[PDB]
């Protein structure tokens, strides 16, 4: 069976060593030229592995690990691939000694659980009630982005949004409730929380539309205003009963799902809704159908008979903010006690490249803050947590017995690959920098604190946990057969 | 091909086909999986089905299918016996050709050797009715037990042994002894078990009696004569070179004649089921033309061409008609029996799986052919390999008294009969050469008797204690077809196969 | 020549996919398609075998074997193919250096499986301990099954008859040991449990209704008017009185069949068909009573309670399997005579007589009683487990070695080869555990050989420990299901001398 | 496939037997063999074919050793023993397909060969050597296969009277190597001299001084040679050294009373010096030189003497005994004869002298009389005679076919195949004669049922029983040595 496993380990090691050169901002970028002629350039490991079109079945598992790495911790997509390949490289000599992979697989899961308690003892205990470390966490994380002076203004915006939805025992919080709507125009200095909800499009620009209404109900409606499609008074008669049934439930906000099949609202219906001051917002994306059904607590309504008053939400004031090239509609005071208020922030800027990278930069800032919700505390990066674990495993490896005693020795050696790569990508000598870190380890422990470089504990914790089960599942498949 | 070529190739071509069924010969043989193109899937060791599925371009093996097709009507269970016996004659015929003997002498030489061995077996044969009459029942019960021992039927075989006895007797006469396979219907459906299988004395037609409100059982109606059934050769429709008035005129002919159920070849309208519901007169639809003959013969009916030709004498009369629910199947079929002996017998077998039904169907059908040969000739012989050993010693001993060229043709016939006991000895786990010499020594110095190869594990000879008998007409039919086949093969010296366009 | 390799070596490659997937620590397999994006990773054995197209025509036989096992229970399907693969792997040595008939090897498995099931029964444990709480919960479960059924009228009386119909059997719980009688002219509340084997028909006319020290013999023959269909015969006789001579000659031949019965010393006879007056009148002087209309179950169930045999023929005089009963009593209830047996030797059975007021209540009560008794009978095969972790696998090897002592020359190597496949189950389980399988299985056989039958292999500590202290057990029903499935699957494969490829549908 | 290696040798052995099968009988088909040296020879004798065939096959060479022992023991049947050997090999092919081990096949041949001898002796008519009328007609029929016919009547008593003197009783094996056929130029067939004492191959001294005849002489065997040493007062010095060396050898001869001496022929140096003949001429000592090296071992047996390598060990007890020694020349022969040896250890060894003019006379006569002595030798060791032509082989196959049912097991089937393997000899005789193969064989089983050995007796065809006995015995050991070889490898 080793011919199947050794061929997969060597194939996966070459992929991990290739992504290893991309670690850090100074790392070596990888280029992928698609068959259609598109060429992408970036250091993101999740983007490289997705567009590489890997034909190796076991090597495709790194895409699922990198996807869960950004969804849970939010950082370390490149580091988790390096740690996965580090265990595979050390496993080559394990098979030569006659070691069965069960002991190899079971030792990785047992070492991952013990490595968490080691990091927690060396980590500093912090609380979410103190806003001093919360603002500095998101401010220093934006030093890798074009924004510099505006990074301090968006720092308290991300802190106050998470602390309200974090509570205490909620633990993991769904990130789908956070939607950043980007639009050309405006600037970064103009920000509005708008905890009620934020849509992705503008309102009706035609004549007669009020565009503003107070004390209205918001609900999801999949219907569409169109003439009969299997004379002027005949089409107006068919549209009269449509607007009359909506008036029965006093629904002043009509959200129509965007579809290329038919139109949205007929021009004849605009004059009918203008008398009742019923605001209509069209071009609702399919992704926003599930988003609006959560924070607003409404239900999608397919037909006109399914439309009821009990499925309609509540909106205190609905108005269209006047701005250059923006025209964003805001809703405040949804008055939903059961569902938590959603967080949607509008991103504005003159250049299209601004609102793009800004949206991606805020996603990584919310994940790092969310790491403190599940497990409080942080550990400074730069190879500190990787070396600290190997220091404790030196004396602990002698306390074991049997085949597992040798695994603890190789497990600490594979952890040194991460700080070694960080020293190589910076131009410094690999071994020389690592020896200087272990020399001062007798006095200093976590000391990078003066450089304002901080990392959450969940990234270092999830990187070991995901890489432990990854390599564990690799050795489980001893054969590959064609099944169709 | 030429003489020096085809004559050598015809011997090797028959050995390749014969050696395939040598492993499946006997109850210890192999059950092969076969799938018909019609979608029927079954597993059986019957050689007639295995040989029929063989498709090959060699003209030597094609004669086996042609002979097995005609033998299937006479017996059908001797397919594996004739092919192996006929191939044994070709093995000894190859040596006679190299000695300078013409191939026509081998064909005519086996004719006198076969007829001489028949008279020798009749002298040592025993009769059933002339010996013990009460054992005649046990002979028919244990005859099917041997063939059913290799199947799951062997668990319930005690009850199924009596079902095969009455099915053959009903379609035959004691003096005539004529049994037709078209008169014996073999059917089965999925669901249930084999313990609920019963014998049916009449047709089935798989009719649910249309609307369920109709009575599922026919009443005698104050001691009437049987149950009258209607047979119509004309479809149900108004006459064409008002439609409700024509429906009331045709139903009156059924009520006046007393026909309880109406059988027609064509479908009925929805109004027909409404008028027949009030009078409790069930209807039958979609009956084939071939199945119309078996109804009038068993029920003593007649074919009525027109509407007004009905009468009490032309209506088929049966014992009764009842609808019995079988398991969870929604078909809810019918069973029509008769007090008097009819010419039509329908076997009904149920099983938990479709493959189980077809497996027990052909296994039970083969038991009907064995009983068919037992009732044809009251005199039976001891089988299991004893028939081939006894008939071989008579020909080999008389071969020295018969001089001429045929003297060596008789020795080859005696050695060819030894192929059957040596083949069964290999399938039973015994030495084929040691057993053959053992059977000849016990029948010479001790006493003259019939001792064959052991089908079941035992420690010694003399299977006669187990009362294992085979029909004389069944064993005689095998040696006649094997001899005729060996003669026909020698009559074809050339293989002509045309190409394709 | 290649048919044996494809049926043996070719079948191993099919079982190799499910070989390493057995057990919670077992390995996994990969199912890859042409697009490779639809693949999945799972340890299910039934999914891998059905998804992979098999060009091997002999591999389709094991496909239908897994489908039969899945109907019984959804667990242990993987172990059926693995156990069947070990029997086919050792079949290579059964040919070259052995030369033994395959059916004789299969017959050796039946003798080994008979001792293997008996060895697991004595070593089987159960949670039935403290039956006071266990027997009380049996009547409450039967009352829950009475919903929608006419038996819901009275829960206490109707469920009590079903409770005593199970535990009092002390044996096989199948419905073949339970007799059901459907009668008319009564109420369902008057039904009671009686073991006297009550049937509808009577027997005899001037014979007494009480029999003491009865000897029961079961046989099937027609002694009265054979060849029931006389249509078509031709009788050629010189006189009318000469035609009856053939019928009178048959009566004289009846003494040969009666003499074999009289030498057995039996006062009770069993017959499915009728009997003429003359052979019945001769039974009066001998005191022989013949029971009629025994159907099929009545023939088989009588041999089970009385310890009889179902054979209808006599292979030798004064040798047969005979039963007996103390008292045969004939009573009459509901204007019909009944037959209540008493004092059956080692009789274990029960007969629930359902007395209804119509035909509709009889069919609904019989079908509802079988569903209620099926739940109670399921508790015998459920929750009852055996010691696992190599224990039960090694214990079966000891029973095979017992039969391997006294054996003939043909089955000597066949029975011994079956003991090697039994030790392969703990060997494969120890393969994926990460430890040495050769050391654990070897030390396990020497320990159980002399004493210590409860020992087993520990996967956590990699040593021999007491299975009762660790609490690792496996269901006993799973053990019999795998052995019965492997015995039927290997019975067909070993008999294969050639392979006929099935027609594609 | 250890057996397939042996099966390849069996097929190669049957091809050699089929080639010799066509040469059986006087009407058989001759075989043309061209030697690598360029010699072209042809004949129907199976012994000469296999000798020059130069078979490189290891197993096929066993037929050469059997054919050599066939002519040395029985003297006839060298062709038929090859056919009988190949018959058992052909029947063993079907035995291997049934799973029969060759040990049972080889062990059953021992019981089958001993049984066929006892059955043949029951139908054979026992004859005695006291009747001389049976031996004359037996040897006369063997001479009908040669050009000499009318002159063969006088040669019949010549071979009969020579064997009866040395036959005695219970002699068992009688070596015919002591009987040598002398071939000389001149004379005729009707002129023959028995000379029962002994006959040499060489003439006498034609020089001056040789007595050429002596009465009451002792003939010894001396391998030495009297010659001058062969590793110009000077002339006489060499003569005094040579004459003294030649006289010293003759001094011990006179004291030993040696009338006649022999000198081994040596072409290297001189045999006997002319001066040595004149020295022994005064002593009345006959000298016979140029004795062939092949006759040294021959004269060491019939004469009862021993070779003398050195004169130092030469004694009188190693000499011979002769009453009269004379040289009688019919025409041109000049041959010396000896009569009345009367030795106790030695026996009356008789050497037959054959005279002829042309070279083809003494040649064809030698091979004709050599086979006649072998037939008579068969009657001395084993009494009785049977009719040849495959007649007894038919009845043996009939009796063994009925007695095969008395056996049990695998060995019983071997008796059935062994009876069919004996019918190949009479079948080949019918094929080589132009008659129909299967038609003549069927007529044999028909006539032999009512009659017993009844016509070749009118045709004067008599085959000795020892030939038919040795043919089955040697074939049983030949086929056994074949099947017992399961493999072969290079060994050097």
Image (cartoon, coloured by chain):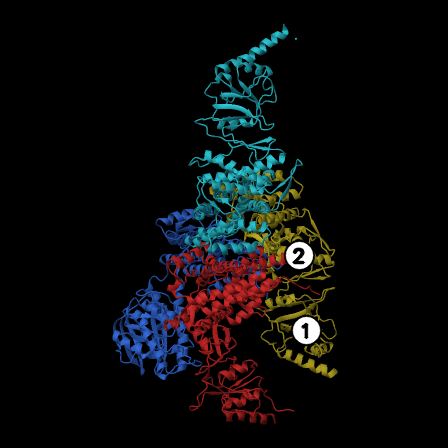
Chain colours: A yellow, B red, C blue, D cyan
Q: Which residue is mark 1?
A: A279
* Position of residue A301 measured from the top left corner of the image (x, y, whole percent): 62, 73
Q: Residue pushed farthest top?
A: D233
* Mark 1 secondary-structure assignment: strand
Chain containing the residue with disc 2: A
In this picture, residue C290 sits left or right of residue A104: left
**Camera-nearest residue between C142 and C236:** C236
| Residue D40 sits above or below residue A463 on the image | above
**Camera-nearest residue between C324 and A188:** C324
Decide: marks 1, 2 in contact (CB < 8 A)?
no
- To which quarter of the image does residue D383 belong? top left
Q: Residue at x 57, y 11 (%)?
A: D243
* Position of residue B326 measured from the top left corner of the image (x, y, whole percent): 47, 76
Q: How many marks?
A: 2
Q: Can you see residue D482? A: yes
In this picture, residue D396 sits left or right of residue A300: left
**Camera-nearest residue between B332 and A338:** B332
- To which quarter of the image does residue D114 belong? top left
Chain containing the residue with disc 1: A
* Mark 2 secondary-structure assignment: helix
Distance from Cα at disc 1 to Cα at disc 2: 32 Å
| Residue B447 sits above or below residue C182 on the image | above
* Position of residue C158 measured from the top left corner of the image (x, y, whole percent): 35, 75
The disc at residue A360 is 2
């Amino acid at each position: 069976p080793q011919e199947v496993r050794k061929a997969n380990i060597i194939a996966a090691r070459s992929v991990a060593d290739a992504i290893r050169t991309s670690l850090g901002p100074k790392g070596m970028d990888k280029m992928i030229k698609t068959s259609r002629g598109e060429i992408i350039i970036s250091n993101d490991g999740h983007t490289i592995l997705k567009q590489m079109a890997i034909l190796h079945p076991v090597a495709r598992m790194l895409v699922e690990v990198s996807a869960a790495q950004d969804s849970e911790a939010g950082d370390g997509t490149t580091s988790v691939v390096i740690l996965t390949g580090a265990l595979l490289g050390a496993a080559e000599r394990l098979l030569n000694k006659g070691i069965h992979p069960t002991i190899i697989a079971d030792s990785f899961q047992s070492a991952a659980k013990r490595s968490v308690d080691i990091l927690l003892e060396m980590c500093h205990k912090v609380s979410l009630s103190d806003r001093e470390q919360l603002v500095r966490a998101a401010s220093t994380s934006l030093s890798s982005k074009i924004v510099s002076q505006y990074s301090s203004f968006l720092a308290p915006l991300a802190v106050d949004s998470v602390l309200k939805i974090s509570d205490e025992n909620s633990k993991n919080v769904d990130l789908n409730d956070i939607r950043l709507v980007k639009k050309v125009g405006g600037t970064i200095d103009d920000t509005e929380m708008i905890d009620g909800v934020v849509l992705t499009q503008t309102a009706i620009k035609s004549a007669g539309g009020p565009t503003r209404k107070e004390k209205a109900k918001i609900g999801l409606i999949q219907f569409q205003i169109s003439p009969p499609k299997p004379i002027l008074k005949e089409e107006r008669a068919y549209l009269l009963n449509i607007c009359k049934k909506i008036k029965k439930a006093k629904c002043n906000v009509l959200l129509i799902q965007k579809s290329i099949l038919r139109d949205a609202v007929n021009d004849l219906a605009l004059h009918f809704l203008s008398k009742l001051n019923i605001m209509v917002v069209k071009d609702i994306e399919r992704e926003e159908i599930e988003f609006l059904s959560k924070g607003l607590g409404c239900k999608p309504i397919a037909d006109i008979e399914l439309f009821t008053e009990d499925r309609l939400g509540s909106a205190d004031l609905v108005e269209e903010i006047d701005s250059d090239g923006s025209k964003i509609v805001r809703v405040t005071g949804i008055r939903n006690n059961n569902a938590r208020p959603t967080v949607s922030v509008v991103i504005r800027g003159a250049n299209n490249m601004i609102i793009d990278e800004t949206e991606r930069s805020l996603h990584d800032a919310l994940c790092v803050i969310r790491c403190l919700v599940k497990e409080r505390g942080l550990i400074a990066g730069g190879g500190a947590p990787e070396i600290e674990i190997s220091r404790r495993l030196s004396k602990e490896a002698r306390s074991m017995e049997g085949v597992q005693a040798f695994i603890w020795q190789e497990f600490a050696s594979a952890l040194e690959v991460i700080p070694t790569t960080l020293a190589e990508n910076a131009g410094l000598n690999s071994i020389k920098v690592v020896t200087e870190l272990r020399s001062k380890h007798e006095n200093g422990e976590l000391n990078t604190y003066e450089e304002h470089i901080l990392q959450p504990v969940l990234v270092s914790t999830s990187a070991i946990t995901l890489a432990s089960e990854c390599v564990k599942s690799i050795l489980r498949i001893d054969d590959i057969a064609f099944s169709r | 091909q030429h003489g020096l070529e085809a004559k050598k190739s015809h011997i090797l071509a028959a050995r390749s086909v014969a050696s395939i069924i040598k492993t499946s010969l006997g109850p210890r043989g192999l059950d092969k999986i076969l799938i018909s193109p019609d979608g029927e899937i079954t597993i059986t060791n019957d050689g007639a089905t295995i040989l029929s599925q063989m498709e090959l371009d060699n003209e030597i093996a094609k004669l086996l299918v042609q002979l097995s097709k005609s033998q299937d009507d006479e017996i059908g269970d001797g397919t594996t016996g004739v092919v192996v016996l006929a191939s044994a004659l070709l093995d000894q015929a190859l040596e006679l050709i190299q000695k300078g003997i013409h191939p026509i002498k081998i064909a005519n030489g086996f004719d006198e050797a076969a007829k001489l061995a028949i008279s020798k077996l009749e002298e040592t044969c025993d009769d059933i009715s002339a010996s013990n009459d009460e054992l005649f029942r046990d002979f028919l019960l244990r005859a099917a037990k041997t063939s059913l021992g290799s199947k799951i039927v062997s668990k319930d075989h005690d009850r199924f042994a009596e079902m095969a006895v009455e099915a053959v007797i009903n379609v035959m006469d004691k003096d005539r002894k004529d049994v037709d396979f078209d008169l014996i219907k073999m059917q089965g459906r999925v669901g249930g078990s084999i313990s609920d299988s019963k014998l049916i004395n009449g047709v089935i037609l798989d009719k649910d009696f249309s609307h369920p409100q109709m009575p599922k059982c026919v009443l005698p109606k104050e001691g009437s004569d049987g149950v009258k059934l209607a047979i119509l050769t004309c479809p149900f429709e108004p006459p064409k070179p008002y439609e409700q008035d024509k429906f009331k005129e045709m139903i009156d002919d059924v009520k006046k004649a007393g026909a309880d159920v109406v059988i027609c070849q064509w479908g009925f309208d929805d109004e027909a089921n409404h008028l027949l519901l009030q009078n409790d007169l069930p209807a039958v639809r979609w009956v084939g033309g071939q199945e119309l003959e078996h109804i009038a013969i068993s029920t003593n009916g007649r074919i009525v061409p027109r509407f007004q030709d009905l009468s009490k004498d032309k209506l088929g009369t049966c014992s009764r008609i009842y609808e019995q629910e079988f398991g969870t199947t929604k078909d809810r079929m019918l069973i029509i029996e008769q007090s008097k002996e009819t010419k039509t017998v329908t076997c009904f077998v149920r099983g938990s799986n479709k493959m189980i039904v077809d497996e027990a169907e052909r296994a039970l059908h083969d038991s009907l052919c064995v009983v068919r040969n037992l009732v044809k000739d009251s005199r039976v012989v001891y089988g299991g390999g004893a028939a081939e050993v006894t008939m071989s010693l008579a020909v080999s001993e008389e071969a020295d008294k018969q001089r001429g060229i045929d003297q060596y043709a008789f020795r080859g016939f005696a050695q060819a009969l030894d192929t059957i006991p040596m083949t069964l000895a290999e399938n039973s786990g015994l030495d084929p050469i040691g057993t053959l010499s053992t059977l000849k020594s016990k029948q010479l110095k001790e006493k003259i008797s019939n001792i064959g190869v052991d089908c079941l594990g035992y420690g010694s000879n003399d299977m006669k204690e187990l009362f294992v008998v085979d029909p004389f007409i069944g064993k005689k039919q095998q040696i006649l077809l094997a001899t005729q086949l060996c003669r026909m093969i020698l009559k074809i010296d050339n293989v002509i196969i045309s190409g394709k366009d | 020549e290649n048919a044996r390799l494809s049926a043996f070596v070719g079948a191993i490659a099919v079982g190799d996919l499910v070989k390493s997937t057995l057990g919670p620590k077992g390995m996994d397999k990969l199912l890859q398609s042409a697009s490779s994006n639809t693949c999945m990773v799972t340890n299910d054995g039934a999914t891998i075998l059905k998804s992979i197209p098999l060009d091997n025509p002999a591999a389709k036989v094991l496909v239908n074997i897994s489908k039969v096992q899945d109907d019984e229970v959804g667990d242990g399907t993987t172990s059926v193919t693995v156990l069947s693969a070990e029997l086919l792997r050792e079949a290579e040595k059964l040919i070259d250096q052995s030369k033994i008939h395959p059916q004789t090897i299969i017959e050796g498995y039946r003798l080994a499986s008979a001792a293997a099931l008996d060895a697991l029964t004595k070593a089987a444990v159960d949670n039935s301990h403290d039956k006071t709480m266990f027997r009380e919960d049996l009547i409450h479960i039967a009352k829950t099954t009475l919903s929608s059924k006419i038996l819901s009228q009275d829960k206490d009386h109707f469920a009590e008859l079903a409770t005593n119909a199970i535990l009092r059997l002390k044996g096989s719980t199948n419905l073949e040991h339970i007799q059901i009688i459907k009668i008319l002219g009564g109420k369902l509340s008057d039904s009671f449990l009686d073991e006297g084997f009550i049937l509808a028909k009577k027997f005899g006319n001037n014979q007494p209704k009480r029999i003491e020290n009865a000897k029961i013999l079961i046989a099937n023959t027609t002694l009265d008017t054979d060849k029931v269909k006389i249509f078509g015969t031709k009788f050629k006789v010189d006189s009318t009185a000469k035609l009856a001579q053939l019928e009178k000659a048959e009566r004289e031949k009846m003494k040969n069949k009666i003499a074999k019965i009289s030498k057995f010393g039996i006062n009770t006879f069993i017959n499915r068909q009728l009997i003429y007056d003359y052979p019945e009148q001769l039974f009066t002087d001998l005191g022989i009573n013949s029971i009629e209309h025994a159907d099929f179950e009545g023939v088989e169930r009588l041999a089970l309670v009385t310890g009889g045999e179902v054979v209808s023929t006599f292979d030798e005089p004064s040798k047969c399997k005979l039963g007996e009963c103390d008292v045969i009593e004939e009573i009459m209830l509901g204007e019909q005579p009944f037959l209540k047996f008493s004092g059956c030797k080692a009789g274990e059975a029960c007969t629930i007589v359902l007395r209804g007021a119509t035909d509709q209540t009889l069919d609904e009560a019989e079908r509802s009683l079988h569903d209620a008794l099926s739940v109670l009978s399921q508790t015998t095969k459920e929750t009852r487990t055996v010691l696992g972790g190599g224990c039960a696998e090694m214990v079966m090897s000891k029973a095979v070695d017992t039969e391997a002592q006294n054996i003939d020359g043909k089955k000597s190597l066949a029975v011994e080869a079956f003991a090697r496949a039994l030790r392969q189950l703990p060997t494969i389980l120890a393969d994926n555990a990460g430890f040495d399988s050769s050391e654990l299985v070897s030390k396990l056989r020497s320990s159980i050989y002399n004493g210590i039958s409860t020992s087993g292999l520990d996967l956590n500590n990699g040593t021999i420990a007491d299975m009762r202290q660790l609490g690792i057990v496996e269901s006993y029903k799973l053990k019999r299901a795998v052995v019965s499935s492997a015995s039927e699957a290997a019975e067909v494969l070993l008999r294969v001398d050639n392979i006929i490829r099935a027609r594609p549908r």
